Amino acid sequence: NLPTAQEVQGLMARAIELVDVGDIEAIVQMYADDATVEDPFGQPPIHGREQIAAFYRQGLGGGKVRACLTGPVRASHNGCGAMPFRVEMVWNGQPCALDVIAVMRFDEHGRIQTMQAYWSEVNLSVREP
Amino acid sequence: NLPTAQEVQGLMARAIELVDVGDIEAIVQMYADDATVEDPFGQPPIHGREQIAAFYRQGLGGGKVRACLTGPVRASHNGCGAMPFRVEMVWNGQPCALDVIAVMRFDEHGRIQTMQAYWSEVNLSVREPQ
Image (cartoon, rainbow over all chains, first blue to last red; front, side, top):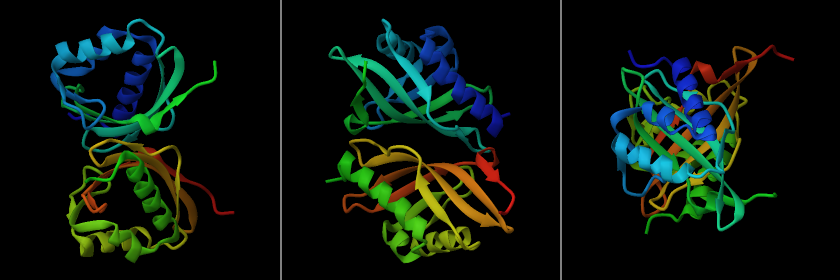
């Protein structure tokens, strides 16, 4: 069946922790073969495990990126959820942080069918070393 | 033009302030005519200012509602954004809270076309009165 709300909470949290450790195969395996990622929402879609893996591989290589939930996963009873988080990464040498909310829809196999990630440069800040 | 990312942040914050004071006429004037709301997401959508007013009236019916952003509004360049917040309400004489995320899309006059609010019982707090 579609994941329960509790299962969505588990899955969406797991997705962030996998980014945090840079586990590309684990990240990719959570997605449907032909999933669609919009990140940032508004930009053209990334489609399918091959392109999604390249997106994360390029983003996470190599390899001073961290990612943290910054609040509870909000989960529905129809296999969807949304979560707030912060990504830490290097743009231009300067340590930076990006606040993001991801919305996910899961299929009946428990895989991510769609992900939208909302953020723009208003959500980007410099960090203290 | 659609609202800029910055304008989206301001609009979505204003939506929370209006819920916090329970000003339904102001809440509803932020929505475009025939706007669609799904709250909680997974329930049937409702649409239009009448239905949306009635929805907010149902959610405000217990009296002492407050609403707080619990992090920054995330905004796109295509008139969309997403925000984390907490509503506090009194339900059956007890102080309760819900953690929610709302996603909104705005039209080119800065009114809301669609809203989706994510939450369920996994996002509830219910405590003793004191």
